[PDB]
Length: 69
Length: 68
Ligand SMILES: [Ca+2]
Ligand SMILES: [Cu+]
Ligand SMILES: [Cu+]
Ligand SMILES: [Cu+]
Ligand SMILES: [Cu+]
Image (tube, each protein chain N blue to C red):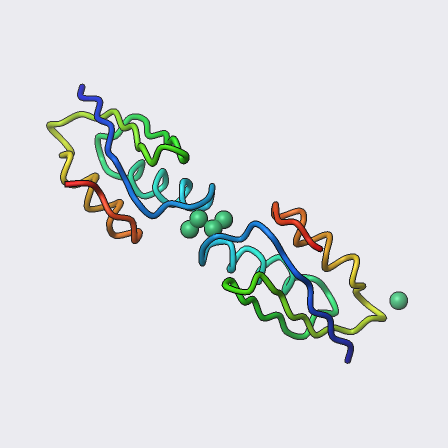
C-alpha cells in the first residue's frame, strides 16, 4: 500500500471536500481519502498496482482544483 | 406572488450556491430562487400562503449559512 498527501488549491468548504473524497474514493484501489480543508491537504491510501498518484491528482483537477506540481 | 431578498453569509463556491438553490427551491410554495455568490444575497419568489420568509431563512441556515 502507498499513502500520499497531495497539496490542493481551490477548495473552499466542506462541499469541496466531499467532491474530492467522492471522486478520489471512486478510483479502483483507493482505500481511504480524507481532507484537511484549512491546510489544503488531501491524504490518500491506495494500492499502487491499481491506481497512481497521477490518476488521483487528475481526479482532483477534474473537480476544478489545482494540485501542486 | 411575494418576494424577499435575504443577505446570506458563509457561501464560498458554486457548490454552496447549488445547495441553497436546491434547499430553497424544494420548499412547497417557492416559485423561483436566485443566488448571487459575490454579493451574498438570495432572492426568492414565493406564495406566502404556503411558505414563509422564516421557512426560507431556516432552510438556508440548515444548509450552514448565516441569514442577516
Ligand atoms: Ca397558509
Ligand atoms: Cu466549496
Ligand atoms: Cu465547492
Ligand atoms: Cu462552497
Ligand atoms: Cu459549500
